[PDB]
């Protein structure tokens, strides 16, 4: 993740998009912090409080075996942004808008986090 960023702010910047936006504009806020074009990225069309609430679901196993994953109560509007062409930072994307559930790994916020929910998302483990 970018150096100096809190885990949940990187999560916010990569997966929080309540107001849907075109992939090719939105992906620039991600790739300005990366060295190569991100190949696949999912934007969740929900505010941060409702993903924070997902962290209050029962603990489930993440893909990597951790036990801090949480599934959403239901499906939400979301956009997948798959890379198709370009050399970084001129990344070009094709979009796919679906309605699906998701799974997030959560932990307590850090001291610098502006929204102190008792558990915040820090990675998107799945799109079911
Ligand atoms: N099950 C999945 N299906 C599709 N994309 C996924 C899945 N799990 C993770 N990703 C992608 O991996 C990234 C996870 O971000 P992070 O949790 O910050 O490492 C997201 O940008 C998603 O696009």
Image (cartoon, grey):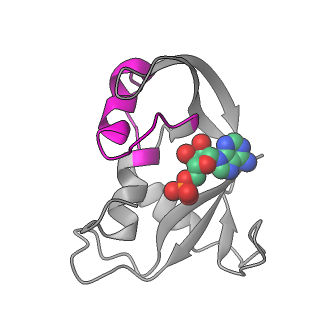
In the picture provided, is 17 more to the left or to the right than 126?
Answer: left
Marks counted in the figure total: 0
The residue sitting at 33% across, 61% down in the picture is 9
* Residue 90 percent coordinates (x, y): 36, 20
Instruction: Say which of 72 and 66 sits in front.
Output: 66
Q: In this view, does 102 lie above or below 81?
A: below
Q: In this view, does 109 lie above or below 76?
A: below
Q: In this view, does 60 lie above or below 24?
A: below
In the picture provided, is 21 more to the left or to the right than 44?
Answer: left
**Is 32 colored magenta in this rendering?**
yes
Placement of the N terminus among the 4 image quadrants: bottom left
Q: What stretch is highlighted in magenta?
A: 14-40
The residue sitting at 54% across, 73% down in the picture is 106
In the picture provided, is 28 more to the left or to the right than 14?
Answer: left
| Quarter of the view holding residue 95 | top right
Instruction: Say which of 1 and 68 sits in front.
Output: 1
Q: Is residue 68 in sight in this rendering?
A: yes
**Is 65 colored magenta in this rendering?**
no
* Residue 47 percent coordinates (x, y): 40, 48
| Quarter of the view holding residue 100 | top right
* Residue 84 percent coordinates (x, y): 58, 17
Q: Is residue 22 in sight in this rendering?
A: no
């Amino acid at each position: 993740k970018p150096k100096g960023m809190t885990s949940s702010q990187w999560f916010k910047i990569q997966h929080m998009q309540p107001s849907p936006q075109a992939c090719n504009s939105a992906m620039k806020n991600i790739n300005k912090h990366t060295k190569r074009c991100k190949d696949l990225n999912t934007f969740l069309h929900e505010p941060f409080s409702s993903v924070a609430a997902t962290c209050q679901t029962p603990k489930i196993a993440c893909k990597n075996g951790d036990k801090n994953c949480h599934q959403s109560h239901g499906a939400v509007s979301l956009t997948m942004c798959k890379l198709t062409s370009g050399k970084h930072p001129n990344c070009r994307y094709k979009e796919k808008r679906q309605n699906k559930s998701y799974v997030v790994a959560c932990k307590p916020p850090q001291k610098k986090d502006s929204q102190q929910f008792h558990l915040v998302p820090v990675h998107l483990d799945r799109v079911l």
